[PDB]
Image (cartoon, rainbow, N blue to C red):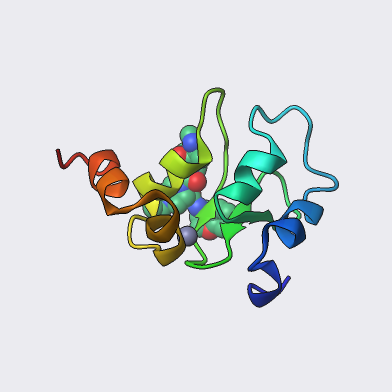
Amino acid sequence: ISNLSMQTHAARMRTFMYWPSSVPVQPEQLASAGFYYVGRNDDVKCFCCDGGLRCWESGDDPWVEHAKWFPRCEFLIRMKGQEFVDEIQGRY
Ligand SMILES: CN[C@@H](C)C(=O)N[C@H](C(=O)N1C[C@H]2C[C@@H]3C[C@@H]3N2C[C@H]1C(=O)N[C@@H]1CCOc2ccccc21)C1CCCCC1
Ligand SMILES: [Zn+2]
């Protein structure tokens, strides 16, 4: 999968075909936060920063996890704002 082909939400959604139903985070929330499914286990990558996330847990919010682990991502900042990212990074 080409990162460029994943710049739009609809394209990212279609990558989740065989996404394990047992994982307690849904494709719609993942795709909204920039992620697409790379086709192994529960591994997803962001189309913009290429950050990879896995081992989704109950109650995870994909935007929070994006800001926790990849705070410099420009798509994250454009969508959620620098204030949000600063707070997740523990700067109040
Ligand atoms: C609990 N919520 C989940 C989303 C979470 O926090 N996952 C963490 C994660 O995805 N991370 C951890 C961070 C730490 C550091 C910033 C780097 N990591 C990114 C990410 C990760 O493990 N990514 C792997 C390794 C790199 O390659 C890929 C490629 C695709 C998908 C995932 C990853 C890890 C996964 C392994 C179990 C423990 C939580
Ligand atoms: Zn990103």
